[PDB]
Image (spheres, rainbow, N blue to C red):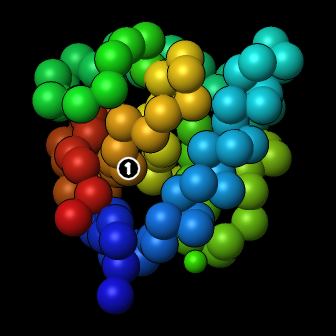
Amino acid sequence: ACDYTCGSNCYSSSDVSTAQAAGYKLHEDGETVGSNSYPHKYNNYEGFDFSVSSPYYEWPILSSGDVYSGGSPGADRVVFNENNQLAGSITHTGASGNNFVECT
Ligand SMILES: Nc1nc2c(ncn2[C@@H]2O[C@H](CO)[C@@H](O)[C@H]2OP(=O)(O)O)c(=O)[nH]1
Ligand SMILES: [Ca+2]
């Protein structure tokens, strides 16, 4: 079973932690990869009720299992704060426009 179901995609905590660990390293180092400059600040326009505190940063989590290193970011993202705490997994899949919804 999936710990997080992003529409069609299936993720386990292991996928979540591994992807977060890559986004936080880049964040701490002040570097970014890809056209959308990842990772970047997640303003939370949606107004999700995260249990960890801001600021939040979003980073692509991939269905392939590979860690994001450029190219298409897909539709899924892991949101984590300054302390390297996971806020949750979200996705563009099932949401209008460029909005997000949390993963099942
Ligand atoms: N929907 C949404 N987009 C955000 C948020 N914070 C930053 N963004 C960025 O704002 C722009 C319009 O949604 C996009 O560039 C999006 O980045 P991503 O597309 O990389 O998620 C947020 O909280 N919600
Ligand atoms: Ca997996």
Residue 38 visible at all: no
Q: Residue at x 37, y 13 (%)?
A: 54
Instruction: Report x, y in % for residue 25.
Output: 78, 31
Taking the view exactly as shown, the residue that stands out farthest to the bottom is 1
For residue 19, side relative to residue 22 (left or right) = left
Instruction: Report x, y in % for residue 57.
Output: 51, 24
Label 1: few (<14), some (14–19) or many (≥20) C-alpha neighbours in 10 Å? many
In front: 8, or 23?
A: 23
Q: Residue at x 80, y 13 (%)?
A: 30
Q: Residue at x 74, y 43 (%)?
A: 22
Q: Residue at x 42, y 76 (%)?
A: 10
For residue 54, side relative to residue 26 (left or right) = left
Judge whether 45 appears above or below 84 on screen.
Answer: above
Residue 31 visible at all: yes
Judge whether 75 appears above or below 4 on screen.
Answer: above
Judge whether 93 appears above or below 51 on screen.
Answer: below
In front: 73, or 55?
A: 55
Judge whether 86 appears above or below 64 on screen.
Answer: above
Q: Quadrant of ligand 2?
A: bottom right
Q: Secondary structure at mark 1?
A: strand
Instruction: Report x, y in % for residue 90.
Output: 34, 47
Q: Would you name the residue on which mark 1 appears?
A: 89
Amino acid residing under circle 1: Ser
Q: Which image quarter holds the N terminus? A: bottom left
Instruction: Report x, y in % for residue 80.
Output: 48, 32
